[PDB]
Image (cartoon, rainbow, N blue to C red; front, side, top):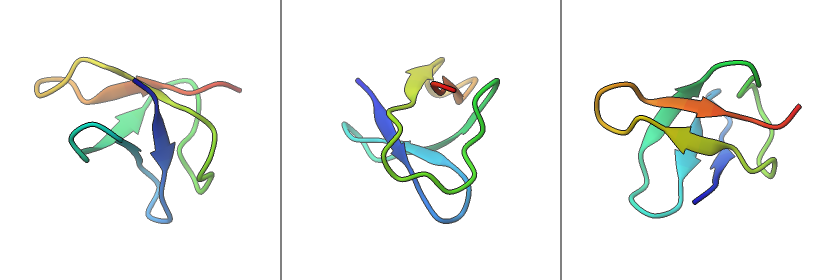
Length: 50
C-alpha cells in the first residue's frame, strides 16, 4: 500500500521496489506524496493525489 516518487520521474512501491508510471497525477519529482498502485505486472499504472 502507497508509494513515493524519485528524481527520474517515476513512483516506486515499498513492498517489492518496482518503478511505475502514473495517470492523472504527475510523477515529476515529489518524494513524499503517497501514490497508490493499480494493475501490477501487466499495466504498471498509479493514481496520485493532486
